[PDB]
Image (cartoon, grey):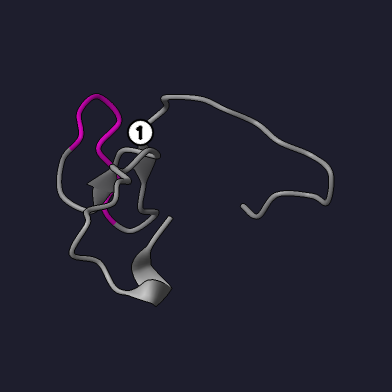
Amino acid sequence: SNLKPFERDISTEIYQAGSTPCNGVEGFNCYFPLQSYGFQPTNGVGYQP
């Protein structure tokens, strides 16, 4: 679900689509909550940190 204002929760539980549950693995339609995030010198002004 979406975060409440001024509310935050952090967990490593794998998000599982309702129609394609995994229940024990990062399978199809199952995504880890965290995704990489970085920057490079070649990035444009809108892409700079």
What crowding class fits label 1: few (fewer than 14 Cα within 10 Å), some (14-19), or many (20 or more)?
some
> Where is residue 44 shown, x and y percent of the image?
30, 74
> In this image, 30 relative to 48: left or right?
left
Label 1 sits on a secondary structure element that is: loop
The front one of 39 and 8 is 39
* Residue 1, percent from left and from top: 61, 52
Residue at image point 29% right, 44% down = 21
Q: Tell me where residue 34 sits by quadrant.
A: top left
Give the residues in magenta: 20-26
Q: Quadrant of residue 8?
A: top right
Q: Quadrant of the C terminus?
A: bottom left
Residue appearing at x 79%, y 49% in the figure: 4
Mark count = 1
**Left or right of 3 in this view: 6:** right
In the image, is residue 22 part of the stretch drawn in magenta? yes
40 lies left or right of 6? left
In the depicted structure, whether residue 23 falls above or below residue 35: above
Secondary structure, magenta segment, majority class: loop
- The residue drawn where x is 30% and y is 30% is 23
**Residue 6 within the segment the image draws in magenta:** no
Of 6 and 29, nearer the camera is 6
The amino acid sitting under disc 1 is: Ile
Q: Which residue is mark 1?
A: 14
Front residue of 15 and 48? 48
Q: Left of 1 or right of it: where is 31?
A: left
Nearer the observer, 43 or 21:
43
Measured as percent of width and height from the top left, residue 38 is found at 30, 46
Q: Residue at x 31, y 43 (%)?
A: 35
